[PDB]
Every structure is written in C-alpha cells, then in structure tokens.
C-alpha cells in the first residue's frame, strides 16, 4: 500500500515507455482511457486502430489515453519496452505509452490495484483483469467512471465520452 486510500488517479505516478517517471496529476481536467495493451493478441489490431482514431478525433476535447503494456495474458507482450514503442509507432500512436507492468497479483502497479476496487472499476467474477485490452474510463477529477472488457472495442466507449467533456 497505501494505494487503497488514494481518492484519484492523480495521486499515482508511472514510468513512461522511455523510462521517465510521470506524475499522473498531469491528467487533471482530462478524460482518460486507461488500458492494458499487448502486441500479439487477436484484439490488438482493432484496439490500437480505434484508440488512435479516438485520440485523433477527441484529443482537443480533452481525451487522453494511457496504454500500459502487460505480458500476463498468454505471454502476448513478450518484447522490450523499446520494441513495444516501435510496435505502437506502426499504428501511428500519438497517445501516451507506458513501461510494461503487471496489472494482477501482488506486484501489480498500484494504479491498477486502485482502479480495480473503485465502485465503477469492479469486475465480474472478481476484479481481476481478465485479458489484454481492458479499459477504464477516468473523469477529469481522476475518478473511475466505467470499466470495459477485452471484447468491448474502443469505439463502444465513444458514446459515453461527451458526458465527461
């Protein structure tokens, strides 16, 4: 801990994909999609393409996307942070890529521990992240407002975004 007593994403920090620690309070005022990514997953193509699309169309409105690579699901993110950064560049990613983390278990990044216990962050059949490309929608105050599973393509989130802009 003491992650459980945090009241906002803005209380957390994480290393970006270039190794620089980022204070997530930079996202105050912005609506964020926080998602765990993988390069060798059947969901990879639709998720990266649609996240890039949403970012292009809504960055000016206040949309930010934080992508956390994670190798806990089928070993579908085996590469280095440098390789993952290159992979993301092939999709023309302009949103924020982070260093690889765990999202489940005792070594999960504390932001992810925290998101999973928020009233709108809880899961079905337990809170654990079930596969690559789970998405949490975070409001301008850093609060979890919705969670979307691996099979819910990012464009499903689009109809929910105006409420938070």
Image (cartoon, rainbow, N blue to C red):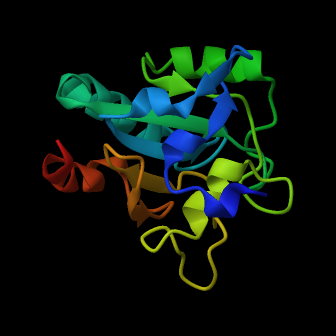
Foreground: 39 or 159?
159
Q: Is residue 41 above or below residue 146?
A: above
Q: Is residue 49 visible?
A: no
The quarter of the image holding the N terminus is bottom right
Q: Position of residue 83 (x, y in %)?
A: 73, 18
The residue sitting at 19% across, 27% down in the picture is 57
Foreground: 6 or 64?
6
Tell me where residue 114 sits by quadrant: bottom right
Q: Is residue 21 above or below residue 131?
A: above
The residue sitting at 75% across, 60% down in the picture is 104
The quarter of the image holding the C terminus is top left
Q: Is residue 82 visible?
A: yes
Q: Position of residue 107 (x, y in %)?
A: 85, 53
Foreground: 149 or 102?
102
Relative to 41, is 95 on the left or the right? Answer: left
Q: Is residue 104 above or below residue 94?
A: below
Tell me where residue 18 sits by quadrant: top right
The residue most toward the bottom is 125
Q: Is residue 122 above or below residue 99?
A: below
Relative to 45, is 72 on the left or the right? Answer: right
Q: Position of residue 145 (x, y in %)?
A: 35, 61
Instruction: Please give the count of numbered marks on the rendered protein.
Output: 0
Q: Position of residue 60 (x, y in %)?
A: 20, 22
Relative to 124, is 80 on the left or the right? Answer: right
The residue sitting at 58% across, 70% down in the picture is 117
The residue most toward the right is 106
The residue sitting at 48% across, 32% down in the picture is 25
Relative to 12, is 53 on the left or the right? Answer: left
């Amino acid at each position: 801990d003491d992650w459980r007593c945090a009241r906002s994403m803005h209380e957390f920090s994480a290393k970006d994909i270039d190794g620089h620690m980022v204070n997530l309070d930079k996202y105050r005022g912005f609506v964020c999609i926080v998602t765990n990514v993988a390069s060798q997953c059947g969901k990879t193509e639709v998720n990266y393409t649609q996240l890039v699309d949403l970012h292009a169309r809504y960055a000016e409105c206040g949309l930010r996307i934080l992508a956390f690579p994670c190798n806990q699901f089928g070993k579908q993110e085996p590469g280095s942070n440098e390789e993952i950064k290159e992979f993301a560049a092939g999709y023309n990613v302009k949103f924020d890529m982070f260093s690889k983390i765990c999202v489940n278990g005792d070594d999960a990044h504390p932001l992810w521990k925290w998101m999973k216990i928020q009233p709108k962050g809880k899961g079905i059949l337990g809170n654990a992240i079930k596969w690559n490309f789970t998405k949490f929608l975070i409001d301008k105050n850093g609060c979890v407002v919705k969670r979307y599973g691996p099979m819910e393509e990012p464009l499903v989130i689009e109809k929910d975004l105006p409420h938070y802009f």
